[PDB]
Image (tube, rainbow over all chains, first blue to last red; front, side):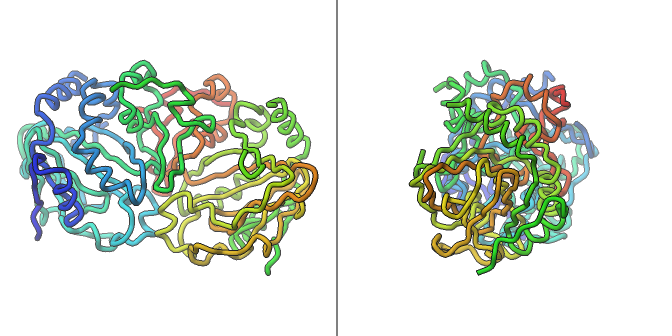
Amino acid sequence: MPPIRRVNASQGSDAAYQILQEDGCVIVEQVICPNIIAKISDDVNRVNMHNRTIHMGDLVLTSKTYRDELLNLPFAHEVLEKVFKKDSGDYWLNMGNILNMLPGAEAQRPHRDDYLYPVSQHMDPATSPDLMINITFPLNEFRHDNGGTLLLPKSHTGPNADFYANAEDLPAAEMQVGDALIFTGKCVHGGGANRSDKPRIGLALAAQPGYLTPRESNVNVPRDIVETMTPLAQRMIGWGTVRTKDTYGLNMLQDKDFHEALGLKSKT
Amino acid sequence: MPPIRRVNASQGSDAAYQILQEDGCVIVEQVICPNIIAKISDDVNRVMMHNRTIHMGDLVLTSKTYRDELLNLPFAHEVLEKVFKKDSGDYWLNMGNILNMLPGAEAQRPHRDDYLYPVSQHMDPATSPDLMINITFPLNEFRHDNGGTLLLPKSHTGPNADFYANAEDLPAAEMQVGDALIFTGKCVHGGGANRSDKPRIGLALAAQPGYLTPRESNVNVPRDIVETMTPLAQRMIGWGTVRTKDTYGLNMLQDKDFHEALGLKSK
């Protein structure tokens, strides 16, 4: 049973990406200031449930720090561009979600996320493009006992299967506020059972190539809030054109670039 | 060289669908009334260029008959649901475009449209899901000499290739105002040479599974126009949630159906 491997963010995004290529998962330690997560955690806190797990989206409206600091985190965009740029091109958010795993929440059947898109089932996982990257920021401490994400490392190249592993056999992502788990959509994984007394809160961001439809649309966000954000974070939440590896533009408006057609102001 | 096969719409959409799965292309005759196409042609004219070929989008804005009669054409949707429902689930428009091919427009190198999405290069064409369906309505007569679409029938199951055919070797889609050419994104095809002296206008809808990002976004179509459209036409233009074959919703607002979270009225 391989371990979940780790690197400090000070060691560089390429180290984290090498482990992500070899294992399909990596824990990056100290990748974002804990105060950033603390603000975000208040925004979320001062505000939809299955298997004792509370899901909450709309983070663009809920939190200015998410909108500004998290969506722009350079380490994450370096790793993401390593993953998507040559095979797929521009990436953007599939969704961003808080997951509040209450006590009594039960571990899920280990699975691949990229099952969500049906094409993944007609491509060879050994040689196919990655369709999803997931970045999870603990909002409180992640341990095995409180349901920290279970991962089968090095499971990202084998064929699609109807069974991968029993959740009891798997290691847990154990990490602190300020760290992040990154796993690809071909990594076998699942939430763990929160067998503790306190909730286990994490902030999962799922990014995908720009040619795949986001699960969560941000068409309801006021343009005034969106002109607050950088061009990159606008693109992340779907307010921008996305180009494929072949420079083919999708999400264009009136034959022009999205920002150009709308006259959308940015920041930075 | 196989011929482009033809059926009349009165023969039903399963007839056309069977020809489309055997051949990757079918011409459906008399599928839509030519007065409908005539109203669309006026609406597009009142709006008055590579390879001498003029492209025009924003048909949702420029034409009410498009928004209403064309995007709801039941024959097209019966075919599109035969192509997409079991393998992919909900479909919606990749784009809707008007193509005015002027005298002097030269024929394109034949190609597969599905190349636009890179995953198409990692799936086996013989067994992979269709990523794209194209429906072309002539706005005036399509002949071989004025650039009628060139198609290589039964080319839809072979491997992705850097070469498929020379345009000179391909038959043309010939059809009147009121017919429609349907072909998948694995059919090898290209625009032909317009060696006539009048232009050749056609209206190409491209549809795809709802999990693939439309090339044309419709987010600055006025809500009040969108609320005059059917729920289906609204979904087609991206103002709707799309669900895959596993009933997972994409394009949702606030963990709810797009229409629910917007309070979007329909017709």
